[PDB]
Image (cartoon, coloured by chain):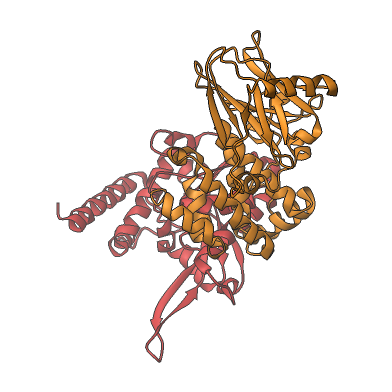
Amino acid sequence: MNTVPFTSAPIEVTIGIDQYSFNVKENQPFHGIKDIPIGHVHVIHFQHADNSSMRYGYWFDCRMGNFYIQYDPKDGLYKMMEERDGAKFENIVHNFKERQMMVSYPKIDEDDTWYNLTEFVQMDKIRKIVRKDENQFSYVDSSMTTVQENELSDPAHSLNYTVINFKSREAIRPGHEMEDFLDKSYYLNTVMLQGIFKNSSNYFGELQFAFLNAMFFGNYGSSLQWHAMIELICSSATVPKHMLDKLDEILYYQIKTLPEQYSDILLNERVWNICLYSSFQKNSLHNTEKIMENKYPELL
Amino acid sequence: GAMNSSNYAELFNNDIKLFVDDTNVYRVTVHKTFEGNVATKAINGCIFTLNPKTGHLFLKIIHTSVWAGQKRLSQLAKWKTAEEVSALVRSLPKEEQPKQIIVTRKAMLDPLEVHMLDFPNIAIRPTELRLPFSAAMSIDKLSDVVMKATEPQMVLFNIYDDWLDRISSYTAFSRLTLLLRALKTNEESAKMILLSDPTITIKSYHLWPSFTDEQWITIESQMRDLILTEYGRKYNV
C-alpha cells in the first residue's frame, strides 16, 4: 500500500483518484491519499471549484518512485512531483498518517473495477503517448489535442496516440481497395497488431488509456481515439477469438463506469450502432450489448 | 464541398473537373424463372464521365462479364466505377488530370475517395443538383455502342457536338441537361421532338441533330413545355 502526500490544499478543488473523488475546501488540512493499491497505474486529477473548465491530472505508478502533490500559486495548479530523498519521504508520509490527515484509497474488496479498466495499461506506454521524459508520471488535461488532431499546434503538449485512418494508404492495400475498406482485417492484424502495436495487449492498453482520458478529463480527441480502435476491431472480419472475448470485457466495464449524465458526448452513436448491430463482430459483444441496451437504449 | 445552385458557374471556369455518374453502370432486366421465382439478367452498362466545360465524354463501357461470379453487385458497381475512373485519371497526362471530381450520387464518395488515395490533391465532391445523366442511354448513339460491346471498351464522345463553336459552356451545359431532363421524364415525346423533321440530320460524328440557332430555340422551348406538362400530370397541379 503506497501513499501520495499533498503539501497543502490552498484552493477549493475536487480531487479524484481513479474512479473516486473528494471535495476539499480552500485551506482545508488535506495532506494526501494513502493505501493506494500497488500493481496498477493510477491517476490523480483535479477540478478547481472556481474553474469547472480544465480538468487535469497525473498518471503514475508508485513502483516508479515516491510522488507528491504541491499547489503552485504562479501556474495556479496542483503539480505532481517526485521526492528523490527516500528517507525524507517516508518521514513526511508517516507523520501525516500519525496526524491522520489523509484519505484512504476507498477500495471495496469485491471490486475489480479499476483493475478491469487498467488491465492492459502500462506506465511505460503512457509515457510514449505523453512524452515528457524528465518526469516519471504523466500530465493530461481537458484541452490537450492529439497528434491526429494537430495534422488537421504545440507538439510538446500532444497526445501521441497511434493514428488510425480508414481512408489512408496505410489502411488500404493497392489492388485491395474495396476489400480492405469493407474488411479492415489487413489493417488491424498486419499493420496495427503485428506492425505497430506488436501484440493485442499494447493495443487494448492504448484503447483503455484513451477511454480513461475521455472519461476523466473530457478530452475530446481521446474519445475519438477510443472509438477508432473499437471500430477497427469491429470492422475486421478476422479477429483472434481471444481479442473478441477480452474486448467484450473491456467495453463492458467502460460503459459500466461512465457517468450516466455524459453518454451524449462520450459515446459516438454511429460507431456504437455499427459495432453492436452492423459490423462483422455484432454477435461477439454480448455483455457490451446487453449493458448498452439496458442503460442507453436512447443512443441506439 | 457539395455542389449546388450557389456555386454553379464554377463548372465553367478553367479548373479541370469531371462529373461521374454511375446510374447505368450496373443494369438488369428482371424476369421470372421456370419455378416462378424472380431472377435478374445483367446487360451492358456504362460509366458517364464528362468534363462540363469542354463537352468531352469518357464513356467507359461495363461489359456483363465483369459481374461473373460476384456477389453484392450493386455495391460492387460503385467500387468498379471508382476503379475505372481512377485508372482513367492515371491514363491522362498530368496537365489533363482533373482538379475535382464531382459524383452525382453520394454513395460514390467513399469508393472513389479510396481509389483515389494516390491523388490527394484531386478533390472528390458530392452535389445537391438533381442532374439527369441517367438518361444518357436515351441518346441513341450512346446506347447502341454500349449494347453492342463484346469486351470492356472506352469510347470518347463530345457530348456537345459542335455547339461550343457558337455558344458558351454555360449555355451548352444548360441545353444538355434540358435535353436529358426531357428524355428522362418522357423519352418517347422527347425523342419525337428531336426527329420529327426528317430534313434535320445527325452528323456521323455527332449525337444530336444539326439544328440551326433558331431551331434550337424552338427545340428548347418544346423540351421545356414537355417537362412542365409531365409535372402537372405527375402531381395533378
Q: Residue at x 43, y 38 (%)?
A: A261
The spot of residue B104 in percent (x, y) is 46, 50
Figure chain in orange: A
Q: Residue at x 41, y 39 (%)?
A: B4
- Residue B190 located left or right of residue B208: left
Residue found at x 59% / y 37%: A106
Q: Which chain is red?
A: B
Please state if A107 lies on the left or on the right of B204 as rendered. Answer: right
Compare residues A190 and A19 and report the one nearer the observer.
A19
Viewer can see residue A144: no
Pick out the residue farthest to the front. Answer: A98
Left-right relation of B11 to A208: left
Residue positioned most to the left: B237
User: Percent from the top left, x then y, of residue B115?
Assistant: 63, 53
Q: Is residue A100 visible?
A: yes
Which residue is nearer to you in this view: A265 or B51? A265
